[PDB]
Image: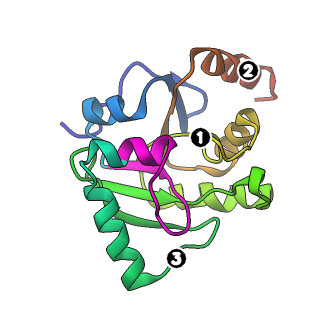
Amino acid sequence: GVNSFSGYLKLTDNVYIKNADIVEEAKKVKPTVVVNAANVYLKHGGGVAGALNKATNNAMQVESDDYIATNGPLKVGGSCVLSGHNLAKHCLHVVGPNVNKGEDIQLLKSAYENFNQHEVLLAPLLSAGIFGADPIHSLRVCVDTVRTNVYLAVFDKNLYDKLVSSFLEMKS
């Protein structure tokens, strides 16, 4: 059935983490909500966005282009709910700050706040990829902001191992 999450480490009651490829995990879990690491015009190139879109055979991009034509661009820190196509029931497209490009890291909390409208989500860490936020900081903001249940997928083994070990050094 849907939301078949298993094999995660519970960091807090709210936040779970796994070393996984989010696309493969979405196919296995059938989440009601997968989070995309989006940008304001929903141009899904590269990173998680490109990978999710490719796995939908570009259906996500076609739908996103229609969303933009009928709603305009998002703002940094904002989100929209669109179809999850074959990957999920819905995709929550969330725009975290691109700090390598001179967007304010302080907007990361507002980006995570979008998760609080959904009871269960499969998600990447926000503002990682080529966006430039320190992943441990992104995880901290996630833990301190999200109040539903988020299942985080971290691709690289070394980063996963570090996030766990570094997170466990912080005050509980």
Q: Residue flagged by tag 3: what amino acid is it?
A: Pro
Give neighbour class at mark 1: few <14, some 14-19, many 20+ (Cα, 10 Å): many
The residue at 35%/49% (across/down) is: 53
Give the labeled residue for mark 2. Answer: 168
Q: Which part of the image, by quadrant, shows the C terminus?
A: top right
Question: Nearer the observer, disc 2 or disc 3?
Answer: 3
Q: Position of residue 45 (x, y in %)?
A: 47, 51
- Magenta span includes 106: no
Q: Which residues are magenta?
A: 33-52
- Magenta span includes 37: yes
In the rendered view, tell whether residue 58 sits above or below residue 164. Answer: below
Give neighbour class at mark 3: few <14, some 14-19, many 20+ (Cα, 10 Å): some
Q: Which part of the image, by quadrant, shows the N terminus?
A: top left
Give the labeled residue for mark 1. Answer: 125
Q: Position of residue 100 (x, y in %)?
A: 76, 50
Residue 152 appears left or right of 118: right
Q: Earlier in the sequence, mark 2 or mark 1?
A: 1
Q: How many marks?
A: 3
Q: Tell me the SS state at disc 1.
A: loop
Q: Position of residue 164 (x, y in %)?
A: 66, 20
